[PDB]
Image (cartoon, rainbow, N blue to C red; front, side, top):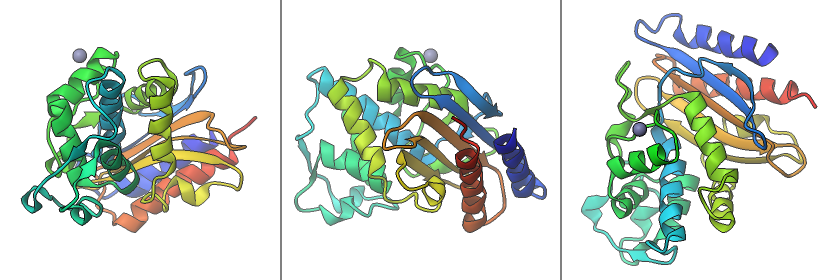
Length: 270
Ligand SMILES: [Zn+2]
């Protein structure tokens, strides 16, 4: 009840004077069992923003497992392929990057060109969506490339998920049989090394805890985070938080998410 109070308070603060569709969504799952521990608007849609990049690399790893792709395959590209927010890819115009390096860049640094390059390797947004639907997530959809997929037009379902869908999908990728044990470990390792989510859940994380996460930010107030975390050096729950529609600035939206994190940590229970 305490984390749920905070999530409602967060939404009230962020949306009161938005003058457009505005919401917060949250779900917490038991990692081992998949049991839904608590939720707030679990079945409402939100823009994924860069949180999709985990699902993208899941699709890539599936192809690697199937012998259709190699972690070490090198991809070259041109300066004209670089889109907004390409901190890693723009440093490798000469050398290109391997598929492994691209996934590290997409997940750990939120590199947009790396995501587009990876989308190409699997056949585009439609094939990411196909991969998701084929593993039983018929809600999540990627429709556009970077950066247009961050547009966050109110109530547009393009490039959206639901908290429950994302959380359930994340659980299947990280601990189910969709990927080999080696690939599922690679996926969580990239998330563990996330470099660009400090002001969100990581800001509330106690010493000794494990976190593997991926953040997102888009237009029209959109912000979110997906995570696997737990005490004692191992993840034991999945957390997904999304918001869209607020007119509040970045730092304020960050603070509200970090506050939800602090609550869910304080009130973790056994
Ligand atoms: Zn479907």
